[PDB]
Image 1 (tube, rainbow, N blue to C red):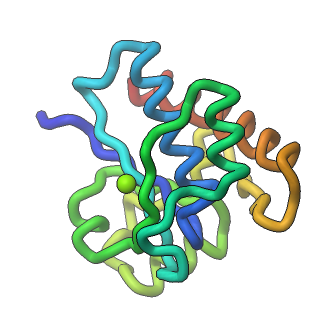
Image 2: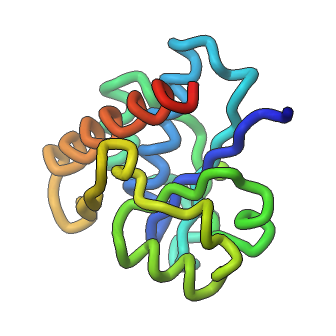
Length: 150
Ligand SMILES: [Mg+2]
């Protein structure tokens, strides 16, 4: 069986989802699982296509050694077909994915389901500390994802 494909999804793909991808990439390295997983992140919207992640996101990832070259892009029908796990940040993201691609019925779910449910709050209107809070919330969810899938 081929490597498991994971796609993190938020609205703009410049804050929460790219941070989730950076953290995941870091964990794959520490656990020696780079040969078993593939990861990327995308947004439901197209407002930021082609842009790098938010400066606050880049800063926090650099602080934790989880930065990577990210380019924001918008989720496509191909993504829904190709990825095995479509992990969204909150319920609005979840409803939006299902609206455009009902075909993702079984594989899309809240990233925090790994910890029994919840939504990762949007830090866009906050400051660096809100971005750090998002980082650790995502870090906890992904360590659990790898314990169960790794
Ligand atoms: Mg990418």
